[PDB]
Image (cartoon, rainbow over all chains, first blue to last red; front, side, top):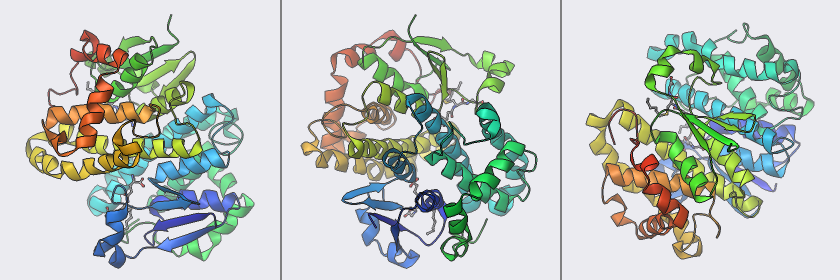
Length: 209
Length: 210
Ligand SMILES: CCCCCCSC[C@H](NC(=O)CC[C@H]([NH3+])C(=O)O)C(=O)NCC(=O)O
Ligand SMILES: CCCCCCSC[C@H](NC(=O)CC[C@H]([NH3+])C(=O)O)C(=O)NCC(=O)O
């Protein structure tokens, strides 16, 4: 594999980049890190910001999940057709990251106490993405332009973990609903999503979702 | 008229890095200031994609998201490394910067009185990675990545400046970051901007805490 992913045995911040690699027909190696090996301290001290994931592309070593996504977007051509599209791809990815940050905070620090409020506020957080789709060819292709981008995989991951969190949360959004159906049916991605390496890994660290 | 417009509250906040980049690159731009009062009316907010500022216009291209604005400018002004490897390291630095900015913002706006002491205590460990990056790039003598300035240097510069206001002397434990701040603040167009009323006379954050 020109690629190595180093991470804990969870989907978490590596699900989108794994979907991207599978859908793009790329091979990669998973190096898993147990809470025991990490807890020790050795690898953590060697990680730039003391966190995972860690990714290797040949001799290039990178940290930061959005950095890995952008790198694969640049090198495999999933970053829009021109600078204008590349800017909009970024804009969608940063909006996905902002919601992902709220989700992680719910999961890891206020699950049973914050859940109902999170779900109640959910439709307002997803509307921007339905609006974006509505402005790009009636929401019949991808989030930006008419070719898939790295932001499509991150957005897809985000919508799917939110349907696990609040079943039917996309029922009120036709374009977002259809987009998930369509992307999930791309041949290589459909196979990946149905596979044990994806299905049998917990979404998060602590058993909550 | 300038092709660029920045729409934001009258604070340095998340626009300080992108204003330093435009000033340093000798670009002109227009500022459209939104008062707390205009924002409470509610109409401009309902029109923003994610309900927040900043908002930036390049010609008819309207962008939201502070890091998206930096990356767009990095692309169009040639401040994104000399090749693909360099762009990925630029991204890695910027995301590190954003992670620390997020913690800084949380402190300033939701826990300043009680969290300031723990935050300052944990700071050296949050700044070390940037000293390390500098140490690996030509002995910390040039920029954070490669040997041309990138958008990440401006964002990193702002983050280091606001942390020197929060914990004066916090960079004394970091020789490469200290010299780097002094070397960048000395660039002719940037030095002029940093000492001008339009920078100096805006508060760093919205609530009187810094
Ligand atoms: C063990 C439970 C599994 C939980 C997985 C959640 S993500 C793992 C967490 N890493 C991050 O949060 C990385 C954030 C970084 N901004 C990125 O986007 O890559 C970490 O390494 N934390 C370990 C640490 O901080 O030491
Ligand atoms: C007058 C107070 C000073 C403003 C605080 C500094 S940033 C303002 C805040 N915007 C953001 O948090 C932007 C986060 C966004 N991820 C970005 O990187 O651009 C906002 O628009 N908030 C307004 C709102 O959310 O309604």
